[PDB]
Structure formats: C-alpha cells, structure tokens
Amino acid sequence: REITPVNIEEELKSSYLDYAMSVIVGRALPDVRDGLKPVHRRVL
DNA sequence: ACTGGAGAAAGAAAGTGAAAGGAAGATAAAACGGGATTCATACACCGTTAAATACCGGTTTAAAAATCCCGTGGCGCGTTTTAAAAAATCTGTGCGGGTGATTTTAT
C-alpha cells in the first residue's frame, strides 16, 4: 500500500531514542581504557 | 436574442520612500583644585617688673524662688495606609562536537 497510518507517539519515541543512543554511545563520551573519543582515535 | 466565459478599464485600499525635529545622546575646550620647592619673615620660647585683680568680713535688698488653683491643648492608644527592603523567580552565556548556509576584489 502507498499509504499506511502511524501513531505520532511511537514515531517520536523511536526517533528520539535512536538519536539519543547514537549521541551517547558514539559521539560525546570517552572510553575508560584509553580516554579517547572516536574522532580522536580515527585521526590518530 | 440570449448565455456564460474572458479580457480590459476603472476605481479604492494598502505599502512605500522621503520628511523636520527633537529629545538623547555623544565628544573637546575650559575652568577648577590639589600636590612639590623657596625662602624671608613673622612667630615661639626665655629672664624682669608695675600693675591689675582675686580674696576676706559683714550688711542688705531687691529680685527670684517656692506654693496653690485651675483649665486646657499636647501626648497616648488603637487602627489604617504606604513606601522600602528582602526573598523568590526568570534570562543570558559559554564550553565542544554536529547540521546547514553567506560576501568583496583583479584581469
């Protein structure tokens, strides 16, 4: 089908949780073993 | 003749670029007030003495202090207003990885 209904709450929750998890685990926090963010490690 | 669509005219309402001016700012010239020198000159400290004043004894008397009656306005109480100070609540902002965009010159 071209059109499928969807509730707003589920879409909002899923999108925001995905973005929050991505930011928390991949962009802003350092690792305890080497103290580096992914960008620093990739540059090095 | 009549109908309904379409294009052109005409008219009225809204947005526009330009407008003195005036309170509200801003910036200089001027008048002011507060320190460093430089002495001459008037001021501070020390012996001498004639004179002006403080002090005692006893009156007194006129003036001020003490006392009584009363009739008021000036403090005191209770209850409201009203600014003033204090506590509570909002508003910005920058740190570092991410998303997406702007402008002026030469040949």
Image (cartoon, grey):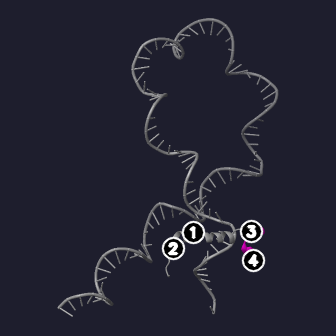
Q: Which residue is mark 3?
A: A31
Sequence-earlier tag: 2 or 4: 2
Foreground: B67 or B55?
A: B67
Residues at discs 2 and 4 both on one chain: yes
- For the point 58% across and 71% down, which residue is it? A14
| Distance of label 2 from label 1 (alpha carbons) | 13 Å
Q: Nearer the viewer, mark 3 or mark 2?
A: 2
Determine the secondary structure under disc 3.
loop
* Magenta residues, start to end: A33-43
Query: Which chain's residue wears label 1?
Result: A
Hey, what amino acid is under mark 3? Asp
Query: Which chain's residue wears label 2?
Result: A
Q: Position of residue B103 (x, y in %)?
A: 58, 81
Q: Position of residue A24 (x, y in %)?
A: 67, 68
Sequence-earlier tag: 3 or 2: 2
State whether residue B52 is above or below residue B42: above
Foreground: B93 or A25?
A: A25
Q: Position of residue B70 (x, y in %)?
A: 40, 17
Foreground: B57 or B11?
A: B11
| Distance of label 1 from label 3 (alpha carbons) | 27 Å
Please give the count of numbered marks on the rendered protein: 4
| Distance of label 2 from label 4 (alpha carbons) | 42 Å
Q: Quadrant of residue A17?
A: bottom right
The answer to whether residue B25 is left or right of residue B78 is right
Sequence-earlier tag: 1 or 4: 1
Q: Which residue is mark 4?
A: A43
